[PDB]
Length: 161
Image (cartoon, rainbow, N blue to C red):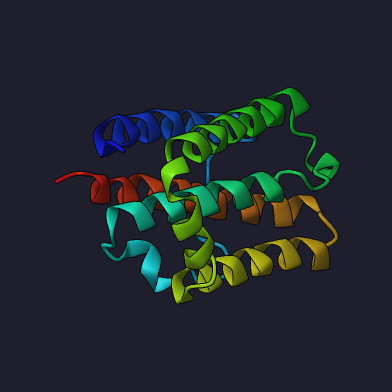
């Protein structure tokens, strides 16, 4: 497995997700009352493979967030579909590339980093559910996901040596 192809692949693709996200509805306002407490780990340097596991986890959960109802925002559903497409493709890619590590990924799925990543998305989803998928909540989440994309680009530094 080579981390150089992967590194540039992810940088490019996550670039496209940012832009697609930005086309959704005006400027991203990073300063809202909400704090979902992004896990400290997402900024720590970690083993190259674990990094790939973490990015995969993030991308799969971000696909889950956009699976929800967003009619309240009046966003063009064709742009969300394109975001969902880009995220799906990266997932498929990482799922194949990381194949020789299936069993290690399975054990990592129960590590402290994985459990913190998951509870973080539980919170993001639960916030949307509690706010009844209203447009304000979606504006808050869009901005948070934007932050996830910024952190995903950061994680790709771990793929270089």
